[PDB]
Image (cartoon, rainbow, N blue to C red; front, side, top):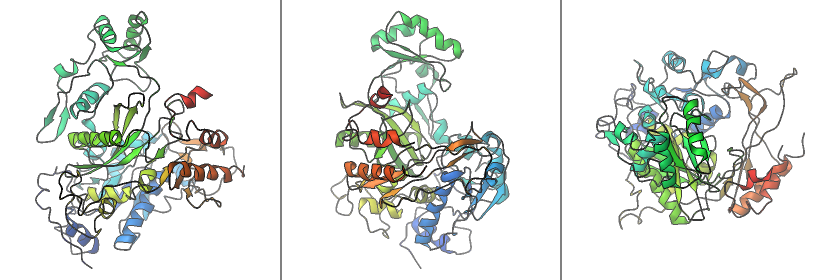
Length: 549
C-alpha cells in the first residue's frame, strides 16, 4: 500500500533526544509499520510494548492498540505487547496477562514491588527488548523518573506517555499554582495570587520558579500569613505545599482560630513552606481533557463534570459538559492548552477545575499529567482512540497526521495537510469543521462484594458487564489487584459507561442499565441519585451528594 506524505525531518532535531527511539525509521529494513510511520511524519517505530500496569487498565491498552492496528495495517499483533505478571495475578488468571503476546513473571507483594517499581520496570524493559513502555494511570504512572530512566538506557525505551520533564515542571501546590499563574489560568485566592513569574529552561523546556518568587507567595510567619487571610476572605485553608495527602492543612472559618491552626499544620510537617489560600464553598469540579504532540501542538478533547463527589470520590462523571456557558467553557479549554505548551506537556493529560456558576468563573486546581480510567467517555463523544492516539505521538507523528484527529475536525482522514487547530484565519474553516461531542456519556463508579474466603472465583479479574436490555451501555467489575494498599481488594471496583443522543437520554439508558444489573445477587442509591432532578439538569454543586447521607 502507500500513504500521503509528511516530511517533518526538520522538527525532529530540536526534539529532546529522549523522544527519538533507537529503532528509528531511517535504519530499518522496509516494512509496513515502517511505512505507515515514515510517510505520516513520525521518527521512531514501536513494535514491542511493556504494560507497567494490570487489570482493565492493561486490557484497555490492548483492545485499543489492537483495534487501531487491525483497522490500520490489519494485524492485532502488529504492535506486540509484553506484560508484567505478578504472582497473585497468575492465581486470578487475569484475562489481560492472557491477551498479551508474551510476558515476564514479576515480583509480588506490595505494588512497590513491581508496577510502581521503576528499575524493575526498565530492567524488564531492557530484558524484553521493548521499544516503549506504558503505565496508563496509577502505580508509576505519575513518577517522572519512570520515562526519564526509560530512554536513559542503552535500549532507548521510549515512553508512551508524558515526558518526565513534563512532570518535574509541575511541583508542590505553590510553584504549581504560580507557574499556572503564568499561563494566566484564573486561580483561587491565596498568598501567591498575582505571582506568575516563571523561568523556562530554553534548552530543556524545564519550568521552575526561582526562590524569591516562591517566597513572594508564602507565609514567613503566623502573623505574616494571618494578614494574608484578612486581605483574602475567610474561611481559608492553611496548607503547606509538601502537604502529605491529608497532612499540613486546617480550615479557618474565622480569625481567632488562625494562630491556633497555623502552627497546627506546620507542626505536622516541619521545614515545610506554608501559604494561605481562600477556602471555597459549593462550586464544581469539572475536568478538561487535553491532547498534545511532540511539537508544541496542544488541543482539548472536550470536558467533564464530576462535582458530584463521595467525600471527594468520582462516582458520577458524565461527558461532555453542559454546565458552564459554552464560551465560558471554551475559555477554559484554550486555558488548558495555554499551559500544556508551557510545561511542554505531551500525549494526554486531564486538567481539573473548580467551577462556580454563581459567578460563572472557574479556577485551576491542579494538572494531572497521567491518562485516566475515565477517558472512555471523552473517547465516545469525540471518537479519538486515545490509546491509539498517544501511541502515535510517542512515535513522533503530528496531531494532524492522526486519523481520528482530522475526523474530529472535518478533514479527509487520509490527507496529509496541516490544521489551523486554533481556528485563527478565515482560511481555516473551508477545510476544517469545529469539533463537537456525539451523544452523551455518563460513567458510574460501581462497587459490589465477592470476598476471598476460600472458594475459587470465576477465572479472571475482568468481568465485562454484558447487559441484555441496553444497546448503548458498557460496564465491568475488576478484581482489585496490586492496588497500592491492597495487593488485592476483598471486592472489586469496575466502571460503567452509558451513552445517548442528549444528556437526559444518556441518563435514561444509564439508569435503565443500572436496573438490569439489580436483578442478580450496591447500585440502590445510584438509580436514586440519577432519578433526582438535582442531577437531572446538571445543577448540583459540591454539596448535594454529601449533604445527603
